[PDB]
Length: 107
Length: 48
Image 1 (cartoon, rainbow over the protein chains, first blue to last red):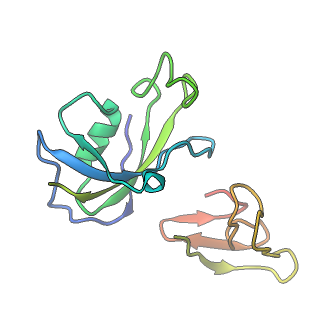
Image 2 (tube, rainbow over the protein chains, first blue to last red):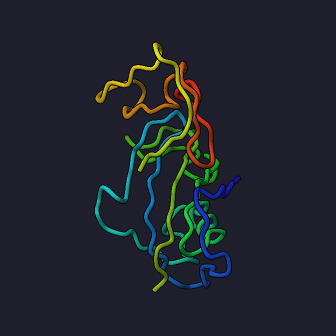
């Protein structure tokens, strides 16, 4: 279950075309308030192509719902993202995730 | 970047730039004595 709440407005018409890389900035944190990753800390825009299973399926679906130049807070159901066993030492098992993604560029 | 608008008490609200409470950077909405919101969501008692 993904809930794409809009942190800020972004051009509604633009939407991620299928089979295209999406340049994003994301700051993922746990439900209780612990922050585990921040793309801004890496100082590089994370790149991923839609239609592949490289990223979490919930994250890809939320990015598909997202629009260019628009930031949103979206929550990923633990069953979707690392349900049975989480990423070792990063996400505990059966724990929900919260993201904050900006779709700066699509090229 | 952080920007809150709201009101506060004269005694309970004591911002000390530093650790504060929770994750740090406590603003007007973080203090339970004070009341304020930032854009989409309101802030009371350091919870959104």
